[PDB]
Image (cartoon, rainbow, N blue to C red):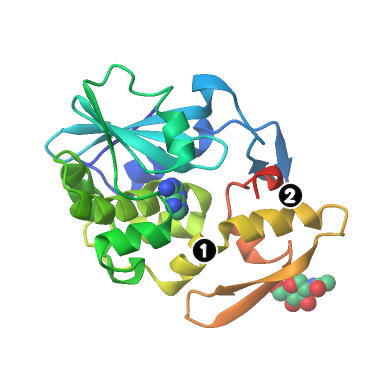
Amino acid sequence: DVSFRLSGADPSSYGMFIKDLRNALPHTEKVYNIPLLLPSVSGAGRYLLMHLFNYDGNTITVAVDVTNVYIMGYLALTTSYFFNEPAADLASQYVFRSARRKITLPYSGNYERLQIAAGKPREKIPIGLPALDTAISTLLHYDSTAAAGALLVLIQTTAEAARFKYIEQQIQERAYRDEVPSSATISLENSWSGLSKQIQLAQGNNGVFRTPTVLVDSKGNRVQITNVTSNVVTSNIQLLLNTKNI
Ligand SMILES: *[C@@H]1O[C@H](CO)[C@@H](O)[C@H](O)[C@H]1NC(C)=O
Ligand SMILES: Nc1ncnc2[nH]cnc12
């Protein structure tokens, strides 16, 4: 499957990892030239395993649902960890079976619950490659409060980067120095399901959105996306959540 090493990492090797991540996700269709994620996949094939190595070369393996890029759980050493949600519970039937013990985290995997658990919102959590290195290290030694913050970092630097070229670039820019995400980054993370839906509805509507998506731009101004000619659609989003899953 897919792998990333913090040791010796630079914007280029990180770019390569995110390309591999994207390429690991199956699709039979591109909508407006953007891969469309499958409505569903049955069995173990539903889950991609990412091998992540911290600077010291310690590893965790992260389980990702290939239909939505949602992290379900991870394996650190001989212990598996899964979010407290039905979908992750299902995932546990298929991944890291050979783990000696299984811990269920005291929270689900969505941003609202993770931010509560961590004690701070994504806006205040620095991200980048050094932050990912830290996050890997944290997840290696169970601590549920610290893990929440680690998971917010991990999620944004893997799944959200795969979904948006702008987020990938934000992280490449933070290769050697962490920084809290721009509001544009937060906006995009928030809008993924909504943009995926509207890009899909745009087919058979002459590339026009049924409902406009309000984003925040790089310069910090609130903009609305109304059609597929927008740069968000042509030059940013890289994966579409299948409408069947919305
Ligand atoms: C499509 O969106 C652009 C902004 O990106 C806007 O200027 C244009 O008016 C829109 N076109 C239509 C047909 O709505
Ligand atoms: N658990 C998760 N995995 C991937 N992306 C997410 N966005 C919010 N929660 C997420």
Residue 26 is at least partly visible in this image = yes
Give the side of residue 27 with respect to residue 109, left or right. Answer: right
**Where 88 sits versus 1, above or below?**
below
User: Please, what is the three-letter code of the amino acid marked with disc 1?
Assistant: Asn
Residue 19 is at least partly visible in this image = no
Seen as rendered, the residue at the extreme bottom is: 221
Q: Position of residue 187 (x, y in %)?
A: 50, 69
**Nearer to the camera, 195 or 238:** 195
User: Please, what is the three-letter code of the amino acid marked with disc 2?
Assistant: Tyr
Bin the neighbour count of mark 2 within 10 Å (Cα to Cα): few under 14, some 14-19, many 20 and up. some
Give the side of residue 88 with respect to residue 223, left or right. Answer: left
Q: Which residue is mark 2?
A: 32
**Where 227 sits versus 71, above or below?**
below
In front of the other: label 2 or label 1? 1
**Nearer to the camera, 66 or 117:** 117
As helix, strand or loop, the secondary structure at mark 2 comes to: loop
State whether label 1 is within 8 Å of ligand 2. no
Q: Position of residue 101 (x, y in %)?
A: 22, 25
**Where 209 sits versus 26, above or below?**
below
**Nearer to the camera, 13 or 50:** 50
Question: Residue visible at 79% across and 55% down?
Answer: 201
Q: Which residue is mark 1?
A: 190
As helix, strand or loop, the secondary structure at mark 1 comes to: helix
Bin the neighbour count of mark 1 within 10 Å (Cα to Cα): few under 14, some 14-19, many 20 and up. few
Q: Position of residue 37 (x, y in %)?
A: 63, 39
